[PDB]
Image (tube, rainbow, N blue to C red):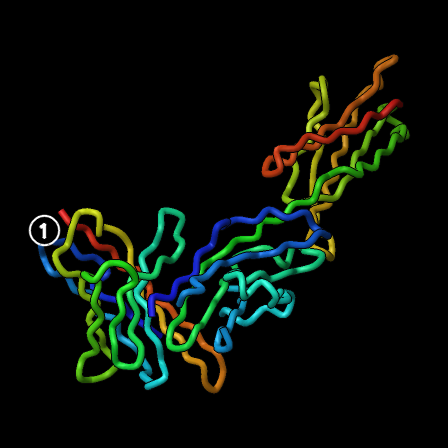
Amino acid sequence: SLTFYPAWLTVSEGANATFTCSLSNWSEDLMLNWNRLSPSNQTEKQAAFSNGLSQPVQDARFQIIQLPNRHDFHMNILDTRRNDSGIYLCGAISLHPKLKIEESPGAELVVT
Amino acid sequence: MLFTVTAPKEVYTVDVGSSVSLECDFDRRELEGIRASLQKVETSLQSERATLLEEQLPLGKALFHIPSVQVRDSGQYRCLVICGAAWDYKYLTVKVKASYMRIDTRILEVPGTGEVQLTCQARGYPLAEVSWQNVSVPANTSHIRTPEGLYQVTSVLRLKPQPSRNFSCMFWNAHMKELTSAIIDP
């Protein structure tokens, strides 16, 4: 299971905002994605964490940092803008032994 | 990597008994290690109904073919593509429909009362409403589910038979935006 907290976060433009994605189980082969929801609740990939590296899709303000306990991650939006306001989640995939995808509940960001 | 998957169409509307081809596109710039799959999300296990048309993979398209779609195939799916140390996915929704095109009709005279009883019955999907054209007396309309998940809708009208009048039962399938009808001559 995955949690993504706080469920609601409100910050002023320019704030460097953080959500925390927390995994029940961490594995070295796990790949972790940070998604945003569209108006039709489609997932849209923002960044990924794989092989110890954070990789933004198209906006480098979206950064993922794995914390020392390996199971918790900070999903950081640097220098927030009003257009960042929306719903986000995290999702993890494992390939072995079988394929397994899990998603956290959504969390809402409001940037004012 | 910068690997992403996109879904050009999010909602597929499918006639029961016909195929779908569910599509997700991916970034070719980001081939041997590509793994594309489709899960039905209800848990989210890999689909046993869909066949990957793997010849489209070189074009940057994951296309999954499901033959003879049934009501139980309706719902949300997830397409997933993994490319090396990266992955992405999209959700797709299959909505199903079945026209209320075959309408069976019956006419009976009700013993004792002198009234006539008119029945229309049809199967389709989703649930149709029935009305009887230019009839003030309300009918009794009900439904069951068929083994394949369709609705069988039955409408029964009981009234004094007025001379030279035909009765028309009108099935309204709101989701399809379809009106179908049958005429009964008593």
The chain to which mark 1 is attached is: A
Number of numbered discs overlaid on the protein picture? 1
Above or below for A32 versus A106? below
Residue B138 located left or right of residue B80: right
Which residue, given by chain and number where applicable, does mark 1 sit on? A12
Above or below for A19 versus B130? below
| Residue B62 image point, x, y percent | 54, 63
| Residue A70 image point, x, y percent | 24, 83
What residue type is disc 1 on? Answer: Ser
SS under mark 1: loop
**Residue toward you, B10 or B59:** B59
Q: Quadrant of residue A92?
A: bottom left
Which residue is depicted at the point 51% across and 77% down? B32
| Residue A96 image point, x, y percent | 45, 85
Residue A2 located left or right of residue B25: left
Quarter of the figure with the N terminus of chain A: bottom left
Residue A1 located left or right of residue B33: left
Q: Quadrant of residue B69?
A: bottom right
Q: Residue furthest top?
A: B163
Which residue is depicted at the point 16% across and 50% down? A81
| Residue B136 image point, x, y percent | 69, 18
**Residue toward you, A86 or A105:** A86
Which residue is depicted at the point 71% across and 51% down? B18
